[PDB]
Image (tube, rainbow, N blue to C red; front, side, top):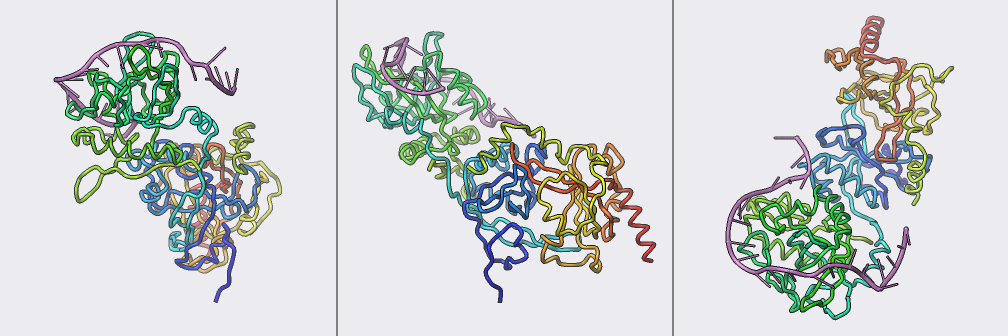
Length: 519
DNA sequence: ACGGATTTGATTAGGTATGTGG
């Protein structure tokens, strides 16, 4: 029987059926579909979400990666479950937001990924691709020093352990925001609660949770003020979560905003003044199940969320589930039809970062000159070499020159914003076949961009007869290919191959002529 | 930028009902 091998992007011909293999400490570079390639809400179909994963043993050419050489292309077979496990929260309610969430996770985290060989059909051919079995977070952002330093002089505290004096004391409180009020004065009221009581705290104005029937006691409702010059920064941080400002939260005819379950890490200055506990919000950071937190912060955040959910009147939870989901990990459960609180939190704990820091420095414009969407011109290079499929796979670097290859067409696919063509060696019988080594025997070739697809179909409308699209299946064609590039993250690309002078028409008529010659 | 010596400093019921975009 077989012998050990090192897992590698090109090693799928060696993978055992139903064996699980492990990518340790992988960087997910990017994925497809994404905002650059599929603008609009292209519905993410199972098996058609693809991620690209680098491991740090693999070579680094540039910001253009090459699947099957220095990154894995990995099919996601159950998008719902992949999103749920990795920490994406908006699917299916919002494709756009889901992908944006996935971007934030992969840009900041490293993952242990379990993959396996999965059969897929190429017309009447079959081959193998990498599929994702599981994903476990391996490493996360380290605690920023600004957090470590600021909480050293603003220690974490429950409201009940705030001990005020004549002189200012500084603290960090994790709280539910309760009210926003402005009387046009010098400060803005953003009051908050812990459900934790303090004898110097006293604020009963609009002191309720969700509805008037669930009170917040006055010695739990911390009156707190923001200096006017600091409101706009807080406003813009919340706006990054709920796409609207602080004032706009108090929309129900009073100052209470608990129907939105907005949670902040408050950075506060406390001082007794004139008989009262005066609390000043010097900073506030929205805290979300996706916002990373230290373990110590979570000790306070977790019971906070538990009390909000348990004490919130049921009917308000029902009316505002989606709204509160911004901050509360609420889920819809099934046999019972009851919202439930999940335990879900992101925690704090170079090579690729510095490559895209270079690209952020220099032009995306240079690489964008090889975007697959850019109209494909004809005469870039003279005396193009004729080459095998294995040679093409090994080309690897953007030599920027045209290539010729003679290949059998296994299938052709209209994917809407691209045409995909699958090629194998010309010298095999029929198209019913199983390709055990896709790395050496299977080349996929694509056409992207309005101008290129218009030339391919002969129509600005992508109009075609379907039997003319697939007539070239089984024909052997002399292709000319150019390397082009597909954007998979803001500063990360993958390399692909695009055909030149290839039209539905030429492929169609060639196919008929070739049949007639053989017959 | 960066840090502290960090800007000021009020009421206590009860009505109505989202999500931030298909």
